[PDB]
Image 1: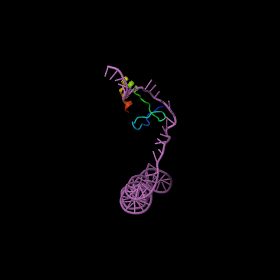
Image 2: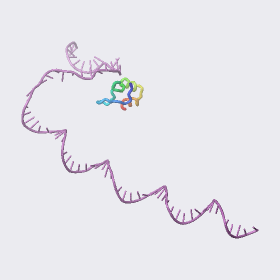
Image 3: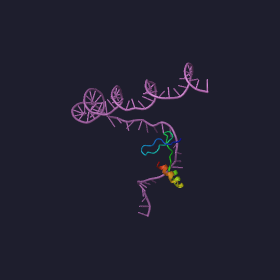
Image 4: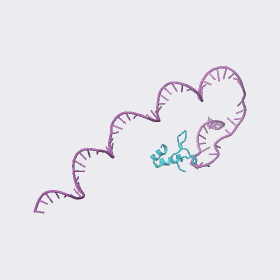
Length: 50
DNA sequence: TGCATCCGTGAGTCGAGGGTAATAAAAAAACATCATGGGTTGAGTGTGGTTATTGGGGCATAATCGATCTGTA
């Protein structure tokens, strides 16, 4: 599976999940912790906003 | 101070079907409202019409060859 840009959820405007509905991968909170441990603030900013 | 009592907590990506149902009353009048159909505005898109032409061919008016019988050592 892979997704560049597709459907977005309705209430919260976030990408859906699952290969069946062509959903994006879930960037959980553990990986957010890992990124802020690295110090890569810009990668986090794009991962949370754009 | 000891007792019961209440109040948060407790993972992670993932897939596939994905929706089901105990019951109930009719009249009448009254009103609201959309639905269609026919008629004015009006808003177009449609179609011919006069008048600006600029290359082209044309006839004038000139011009430079091509062919033979009279004058000079």
